[PDB]
Image (cartoon, coloured by chain):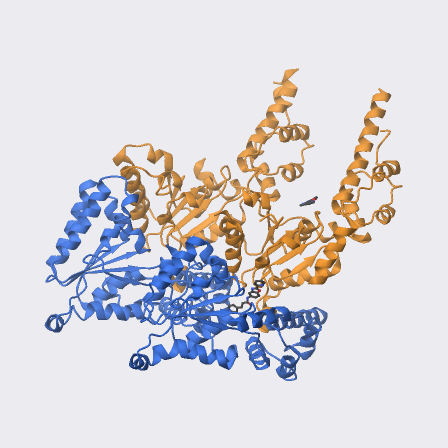
Chain colours: A orange, B blue
Amino acid sequence: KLNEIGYDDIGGCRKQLAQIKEMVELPLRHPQLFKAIGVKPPRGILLYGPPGTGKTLVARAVANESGSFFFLINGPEIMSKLAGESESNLRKAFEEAEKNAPAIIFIDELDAIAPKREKTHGEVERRIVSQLLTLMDGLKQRSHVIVMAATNRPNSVDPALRRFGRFDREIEIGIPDSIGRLEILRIHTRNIRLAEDVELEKIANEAHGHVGADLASLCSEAALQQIRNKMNLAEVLNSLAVTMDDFRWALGKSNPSALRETTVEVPNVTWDDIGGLENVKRELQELVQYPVEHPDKFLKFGMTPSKGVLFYGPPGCGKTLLAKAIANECQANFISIKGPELLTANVRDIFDKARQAAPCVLFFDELDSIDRVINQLLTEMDGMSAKKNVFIIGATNRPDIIDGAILRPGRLDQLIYIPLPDEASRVNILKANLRKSPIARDVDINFLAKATQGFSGADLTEICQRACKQAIRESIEAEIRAEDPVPEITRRHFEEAMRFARRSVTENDVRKYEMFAQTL
Amino acid sequence: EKLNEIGYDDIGGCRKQLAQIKEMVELPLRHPQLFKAIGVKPPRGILLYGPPGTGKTLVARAVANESGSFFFLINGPEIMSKLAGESESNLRKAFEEAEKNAPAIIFIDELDAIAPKREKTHGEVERRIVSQLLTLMDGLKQRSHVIVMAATNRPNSVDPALRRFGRFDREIEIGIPDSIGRLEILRIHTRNIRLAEDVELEKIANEAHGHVGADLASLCSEAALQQIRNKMNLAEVLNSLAVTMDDFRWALGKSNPSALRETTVEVPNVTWDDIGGLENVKRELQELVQYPVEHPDKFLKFGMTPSKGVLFYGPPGCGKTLLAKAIANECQANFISIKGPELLTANVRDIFDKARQAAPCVLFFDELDSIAKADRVINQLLTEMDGMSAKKNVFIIGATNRPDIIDGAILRPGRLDQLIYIPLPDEASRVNILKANLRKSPIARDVDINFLAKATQGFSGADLTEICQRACKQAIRESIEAEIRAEDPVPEITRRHFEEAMRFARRSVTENDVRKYEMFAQTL
Ligand SMILES: */C(=C\C(=O)Nc1ccc2oc(-c3ccccn3)nc2c1)c1ccncc1
Ligand SMILES: */C(=C\C(=O)Nc1ccc2oc(-c3ccccn3)nc2c1)c1ccncc1
């Protein structure tokens, strides 16, 4: 079975799979063509990412597809041997790989073999690390041996290993996105018998923070729930088919292990969902979309584009949603960071993660909360080339207390005010909020927008929530009394919600923001 | 085979240091008669250091090949990967072999792997090998012509006992190449690549900032990869492959140099024409930073030691840094641009030592206010400056925007005796700045800089740059919008764009601030 694993049996990493394919397969199938022009093939590739992804099979998939020899060195297995056994085994591994070429050597759990030098506390451990380094540098330029390694964090690996010529290409196999999750769910359910009511797309969309292993466990739990419901009360053996109810139940009881891991992807929020102003949209377009869309114009006119902006205004979800929408427009990855998250050298880490994604929209929320971290952010921004397509966006609700250093040119040089949404914006927001709900025909959104003025996006969302709570309360009470009288939200529900206006922004705050704008 | 042919030409990015090493090694190892006659003691330990990838690992081999001497290589990890007695036997066997075949050169690559700081060593085998190395080092009789060269990332990671007066007394830094060095490296690596006729490596080298030799090798590889990707994916092809300037630019776009955070030492390419500047300030800086270095004889004749430090205070902007870079450029002295934020994040002495190593240096300290009036850094800097021999051609320049806050200690004589002020640029300065800003971009013949300068008064360097930047964005905006309509209409930036940018003409420096600076000057 192992030799039969291919590209199709790995899900959740298709971009990285293409990268690895071009890096490895092509040289190992037409070495003459690459040598002619003079392209040097890579000699060390380090895959890293959260545990549970498919990065342990990537090496096997590549080796099988390229039809090359494959050798596996298991970190814990090597470190579980006597003093000389580990050295003999590393040497034998590399020698065997050289014997049969082209080859691939996968050193699973490298951080087990070569942890940070501080962690090591014996002569045997350091001797093994140095043995690995010596073997690594000994790969002749034409040996046709590619060393692949996997870890959780490259920082846990001995830095000497991450030098030129030893491990110079580092690829991240991160959390899958919705398409990746669907791919994994379709891979794992190959043998399970499904019912006709299963729509894996919804499951994939709803499974947040799930890695391939988590999805395998989820499928197993759903099958078990089906067994429980059926057998509890050969005929049955042939009448078993997991149902969407079982999958939803399994989702309910699941505890994904990758909840806290930052997510990088292209969000699915469009302009229509926030509405927003026109000037702000135009400015954001000019800043972010044009340089990526038409770099030629910037080059010919020869002025380097600015990197980041700094939204200010009353609190709410407009700023974050606006940034997400602009990122969606340009099809660039979106990275969200919260001040509380940062308070808990991570700054360099997140900046490098952004730099890895070519079009990225690095978002920093609650920037006001953020001396050491401030200086680290300052230096990192100052040391960001204004020619790489990485855009920093800030957000704050107290521009007065923001340190002026960040505002200095080259770091964050543009300020944009985000006012309360207007009538059209409020209409768009309300339409988005009730998008997934069965609203009644009588209800008109335009009148609601006219009635509500000065209400922040939070206020409108709260208004929608109050109405739905009323509908649920009515349905339950009617159901109890009856024991679909309330099939859709009615006007009375919305009016009852409106009974408590609760405007979250005072006119004094708006005047203060206006004064801040005028002073600029 | 190929190893024994590496020479001076096959190393790039280090030409000053290569000349130093040539004089310091090749000549003694070819004409010992003269050196012994006049009585010059050849060095016995040379420690090369710098960021990884710079090609210092070939310097030893290049020198050995050129001088025709025996060459022996000891690889740190290789020695430390053996059993307890194997590493000792190997060090001893290396030095014995080198001495047996004289003259020789011994290159101990990755010294810090063999002899780290005493504290970092926990076992006894590690300390035993370090002591073995020290014993062998001291055992080199002056008569025997053995020169030990070692390479390490930083000299501090090496055991201090090694950096003694008879072991490793010469330390050479091989740091990031400059633009000429980058061009040299690119020429070396593209020897076997077949390039197209539109490739002009000068622009690549100039734009490749923070790249080391290895990074440039990767860049060339990626460009070739892009070319093959496009053409092939879309024997004839094998003979039609030629990298193109588009491929090199694309490779640059997607490259992540590993030496971005490393301080750069180099003569800046900024001239007086790009800053304008008051004639008084220009003359004063000329005197201070040029007469001592250009006519030391006169200073000796009148016997007054030149002051070392100058301060700059005034409105925030690009003026101070540009002025310092210009004065450095005129004297062709190296420029070090330590910023305050970098220092906020031992280090002070390291910067001062780096400056000292480059004799004519224009060490720059921006935003000094943040560091000074904290206690630790300010005291360390005061101590280090006070220990700065005024007879050396190292000039310290400070910049600040709160001249009222800096502690008076820094301005006491012997530390920073001059207190020049940098005021807002005048009309001619603004004209020069605008000409420089638009120099790289096409401009309409109608557009006149003189009127724009006349309109702009009190505008800081950023203000002028902002004006130019805003105008270009308008031109790009208009240029593209026409393109979609047609789907060149805007070949150059027209005066309409400049006037539209001028519509929102803003002054970033309040006249109150300028008056405050004037008050400080008068009180001073
Ligand atoms: C939306 C985020 C959101 O609603 N954020 C938010 C709501 C209310 C807030 O009040 C404050 C505040 C702070 C200090 C003083 C007073 N009030 N901050 C608030 C923030 C959202 C984000 C991302 N995706 C979707 C929605
Ligand atoms: C130019 C650098 C430059 O213009 N930097 C700069 C612009 C504006 C600034 O405002 C402050 C400041 C300080 C304190 C309070 C308020 N504002 N600092 C500023 C710095 C330049 C540098 C290097 N090479 C070329 C040009």
Picture quadrant where residue B381 is located: bottom left
Could you tell me if residue A427 is visible in this image? yes
Could you tell me if residue A356 is visible in this image? no
Of B297 and B294, nearer the camera is: B297
Of B468 and B490, nearer the camera is: B468
Q: Is residue B391 left or right of residue A251?
A: left
For the N terminus of chain B, the quadrant is bottom left
Residue B93: image x %, image y %? 14, 50
In this rendering, the answer to whether A480 lies above or below B448 is: above
Ligand number 2: quarter of image: bottom right
Q: Residue furthest top?
A: A233
Residue B374: image x %, image y %? 46, 54
Picture quadrant where residue B409 is located: bottom left
Of B60 and B390, nearer the camera is: B390
In this rendering, the answer to whether B182 lies above or below A468 is: below
Q: Is residue B165 left or right of residue A271?
A: left
